Every structure is written in structure tokens, then in C-alpha cells.
Image 1: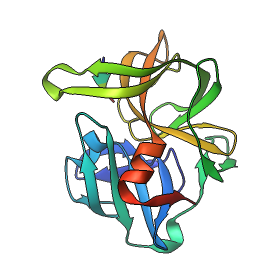
Image 2: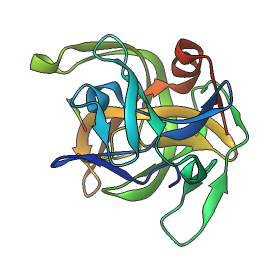
Image 3: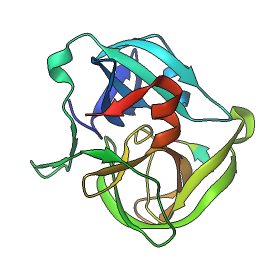
Image 4: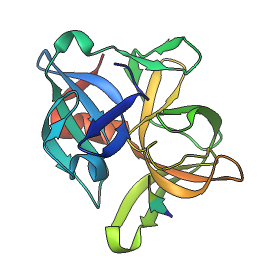
Length: 4
Length: 181
């Protein structure tokens, strides 16, 4: 997961 | 400007989460990983930020007339917001953001820990099967007229689908003594  | 619309700083873009009031003063909630970037935004000045651990931030509007207490649905209509609540597993939710617009799905987990690698770890996140893409962060997670969360991040995209995590809006409201408009 990654920050949008 | 309503929930889900673009807010920028220099070349960076995020989405507005919810317009709120702090002792009668109009502010906007968005993601903390966005407000960490700068104090100066298209809509005003940052007055609070918390990322990682949490993922929320607040901006005081330069123009109080712009604090629209609704969420933009990206089809020329808006959803009126009246309260804030807590999500529950299986709830039908919608998300609005400036990259992908409006998307729907359901809450699949609560209190999720999310490791963003070099960006750090966030705790207590709402988990959903709604897709999102870069630029969608800070945008609105809601169910009808009830505000629930702010887009933080996830995996996948809106073509293949993915998993997304949201900061519960109630923690952000109590951190700043704010109420949704």
C-alpha cells in the first residue's frame, strides 16, 4: 500500500 | 468547494475531505500526509497536521463563503452532509476524490495497521474494497449524509480494483474541536  | 474536490499547493494535489467549523470558523479537513507538505494551500492556510500514526490535517479557509457542507458527486450533483459517524463492517459507502471521481463499495475491516514503507505506519484505519488513485487522498468517505473518513492510501487502482484505507473522521474532528458543516 501507498499514500494516495 | 465541496468534499472530494481538488486542493493544491505548488505542484501537489490532494482532495478536500469535509468542510467543518471550529468555534464558528470555517476550516477543511484533508489527509495529514498532504498537509505535511506545506502550510500554503489554494484554499487557505494549514492550522494542523498529523502524519504518520494518524492521517489527518486541517486548513483554515481564506474565503469562508467557500465552506460548502456537501460532497461533490462528479455528476453535477452533491450529497448534503449533516453528521459524522463511525463505519461498520459491511456498510455500503461512497468515496469522492479529484482523480477518480465518485466510487462505491463496502467496508471490509476496521482498525487496520498500514505500513507505507518510507512514509511510515498508520494505525486504526477503516479498510474498504473501494478503489482510489494518487490525488484522491484526503477525499470523502461517506454513507448518505453521514461523514465517515478521509482517504489515506491503498493498493491497486480503479481499473483493476484495489483496497483502500481511510482515517476515521471522528478522531480528526475531536483532535481539533470541529463539527461537520
